[PDB]
Image (cartoon, rainbow over all chains, first blue to last red; front, side, top):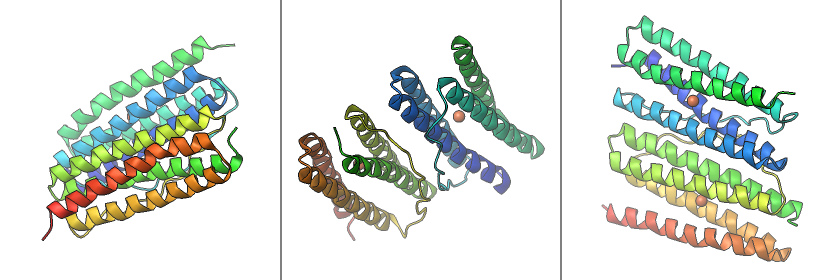
Amino acid sequence: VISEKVRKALNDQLNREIYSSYLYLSMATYFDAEGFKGFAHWMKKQAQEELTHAMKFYEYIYERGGRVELEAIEKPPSNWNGIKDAFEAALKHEEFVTQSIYNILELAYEEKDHATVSFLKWFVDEQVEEEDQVREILDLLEK
Amino acid sequence: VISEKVRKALNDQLNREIYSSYLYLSMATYFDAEGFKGFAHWMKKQAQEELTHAMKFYEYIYERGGRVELEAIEKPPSNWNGIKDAFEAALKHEEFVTQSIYNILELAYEEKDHATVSFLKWFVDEQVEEEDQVREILDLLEK
Ligand SMILES: [Fe+3]
Ligand SMILES: [Fe+3]
């Protein structure tokens, strides 16, 4: 019973979560090249976490009677100017993902799609946590 | 001690294994849309299997002192004309992946990169198995 509009929006987001996963893997390639096994391992966990986010969107879309369409994934950046600069790029990206979700939340509220509104709440909470995990990294590394 | 040429070839293949994973997920979107939960679940296992193939290339490249660079992933097809037509596309794709590996095997033999030659042998064996798993599906579904 999902509108085509809310379905398109959730499919767009599914593809956004796939690119999120690819960017984070890209960041690991930078960390691994620079010898930072530990930051690379962190980025690889994150890349796997975003994939399960994308599959939660995948399965919810089919539960509501929609179809998934996978789009082209753009080439991510492969180099930053140091650790801090990578993680600040991570944080900026997370915040873009959070705004992306909030616009779906708004459209769901508009259409009174109470099931979608409830589905997204988990992703709102998890992005709050992830944004703050990156802030704690940046603070721990300060100066 | 890997040549730039053998490194580029293994990085190209890493990106080929990522697209392999995306094509297989695409095939699942087709199966799931058509109600075939079972063929979709098969394609999702396969997509996850190719990802670990791509990460074996990822970690081997760094073990030999190279860097990974992630490229853009093209949009896969999202529709086939039935089950059999999907799996025949799967088989044709596997065979392209096998030829891709054999050309790396050849370049490794040329450069007497005995470590790469041994690394790829696992992927030669696994593609033989996967190609035959798809043939057994096609035969079981015949007419
Ligand atoms: Fe996410
Ligand atoms: Fe593979």
